Every structure is written in structure tokens, then in C-alpha cells.
Length: 97
Image 1 (cartoon, rainbow, N blue to C red):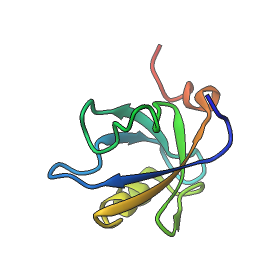
Image 2: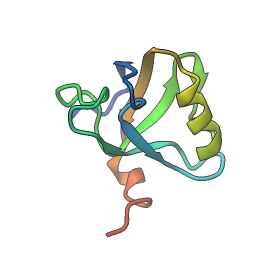
Image 3: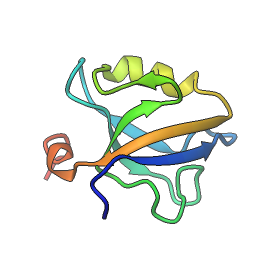
């Protein structure tokens, strides 16, 4: 699985973007914690649980809190560009064992 940043385009559905995010306050990162099967984000493996969302459209989320990121993902439009980077090592600290 590539570890360099990846560009994914999502088309918002009648339920949102099809994934959940985990994070916290500013700086802990925004990570994909769940991807809905058949949802807008289920794109033949292009997005992965454990991806860090580096940005959404023009909005940098590397340093955003969870509350900021949630707001940005909802105001992102019907066509959404996600820059994702696989970092399961960093993500693992958010996921209960």
C-alpha cells in the first residue's frame, strides 16, 4: 500500500461522504476510522481505514481538530477532493485494541 499522499475524489451521496473520522484537538491528525461499504468513499480500496486526511478541497486538515475537520468535510461540496496518506502506525493510537 503506497505510503505517499494520494488524491481521491468523492461524490457526496444522500448520506454524506461515507466515512467516519477520528482525531481530537488540533495536531493529533484526522484519520479515517471507518469506511461504509457501498458508500461514496468505497472506491475499490482508494481510501483506507488508517489514512490520515491531509486536506479536503482547499482546506488543510493536518493541524485541524476533530470539530474543525467535521465542519470542513460537511462544507466541502458535492465533489470532494481528499488528500489521504496511509499512516496506520499513527492511527493505531486512536483505535481500541
